Amino acid sequence: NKCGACGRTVYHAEEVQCDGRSFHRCCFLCMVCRKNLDSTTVAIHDAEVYCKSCYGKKYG
Ligand SMILES: [Zn+2]
Ligand SMILES: [Zn+2]
């Protein structure tokens, strides 16, 4: 439905599933810091999305 960043239309093509929500395919982010995330990886920790950087550096 709606992305955490914009709130434009994530649907099928322009979404990647990340736990409960999806974000847009390009406009894909850390729910914490908000680094420019994409189809590198992604992570989840607890209730929020951690990106590539803050996941591997906070937790190792
Ligand atoms: Zn978006
Ligand atoms: Zn981050």
Image: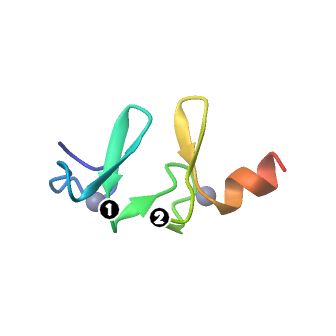
Give the alpha-carbon distance from disc 2 to disc 1, as whole Å. Answer: 8 Å
Instruction: Report if residue 4 is visible in the image.
Output: no
Quadrant of image for the N terminus: top left
Residue type at mark 2 is Ser
Residue type at mark 1 is Arg
In x, y percent, where is residue 39?
Answer: 47, 64
Give the class, few, some or many, for how many residues have Cα within 10 Å of label 2's Cα (few <14, many ≥20): few
Looking at the rendered structure, the secondary structure element under dot 2 is loop
Instruction: Report if residue 44 is visible in the image.
Output: yes
In x, y percent, where is residue 19?
Answer: 44, 34
- 31 versus 13 height, above or below: above
- Residue carrying label 2: 39
Ligand 2 image-quadrant field: bottom right
Which is nearer the eye, 48 or 17? Answer: 17
Q: Which residue is drawn at 20% across and 57% down?
A: 13
Q: Does the residue labelled 1 lie within 8 Å of ligand 1?
A: no
Looking at the rendered structure, the secondary structure element under dot 1 is loop
In x, y percent, where is residue 53?
Answer: 68, 62
Which is nearer the eye, 9 or 12? Answer: 12
Give the class, few, some or many, for how many residues have Cα within 10 Å of label 1's Cα (few <14, many ≥20): some
Which is nearer the eye, 13 or 38? Answer: 13
Seen in the image, is 38 located left or right of residue 42? left
Circles 2 and 1: CB distance less than 8 Å? yes
Which is nearer the eye, 11 or 28? Answer: 11
In x, y percent, where is residue 17?
Answer: 37, 43
N-terminal label among 2 and 1: 1
The label number, if any, that marks residue 52 in the structure image? none
- Residue carrying label 1: 25
